[PDB]
Length: 126
Length: 127
Image (cartoon, rainbow over all chains, first blue to last red; front, top):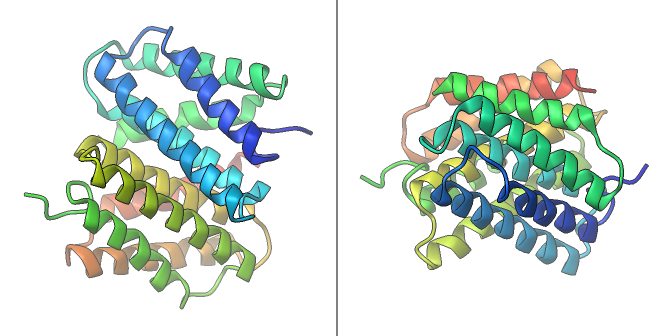
C-alpha cells in the first residue's frame, strides 16, 4: 500500500532515485538531463516547503508526483537531439521502475504506462 | 519576445493564478479538491519565481513546468471523486484555462486547452 506519495520523504526519494537512474541511461543529452534535474530539484524543494507547512498530504503529493513525471515526459517529447523518442521513453520507464523498487520496493506499472502515454501525447501535440 | 507564459516567467505565474481564480467560480469540485489544486498551483508559481530569480526559468523549463501544472490539475480532477461529473470538471477546467489565457496574452491557445481536457480523460481511464 506504500507509494511515492505516502509521505514527503518517499516522494523526494522517488524523484532523486529517478534522476539518479536516468543519468545512466541512453537517449538524452547533457542539456536535457540538466533541465530534467533542475525541475526534479525544484519539485523536491516544493515538497519540502509543503511539508514544513503541514500541507504535504497524499493527495497533494500524488499531484506533485504527476507534475514531476509529466515534466520529464514533456522534456523528452519536446527537446531535440540525444536519441530516438522510443529510446527516451523506454529509459523513462526503466528509471521509473527502478525508482519504485528503490523507494517503496513495489513497481506501479499503471503509473509507468500513464507516463509513457504522456510522452506520446506530448509528442503528438508538437 | 517574452510575451507568453512559455517565455515570460511572470506571465506563467499569472497564468496559473488566473486559472485558479476562474476555477473557483465554476462548479464540479469539492472544497478539498480546490484546496489541492490551489496548493499545487501555488507550489508551481513559487518554483518558477525561484528559478526566475536565478535566471534559470528558460522557455524549455517554463514549457515543462506549465505542462506539469496543467497535468497536476487534470490529475486532481480525474482521481479525486465527489463534487461532480467528469464532464462538469472538464468543462470547468476548459473555462478556467480560457480565462487564464484571456488574463495573460489575451489569446486563447485552443490546442493547449484541448490537450488538458484529454489529460483529464486519460488520467480518469487509468483508474
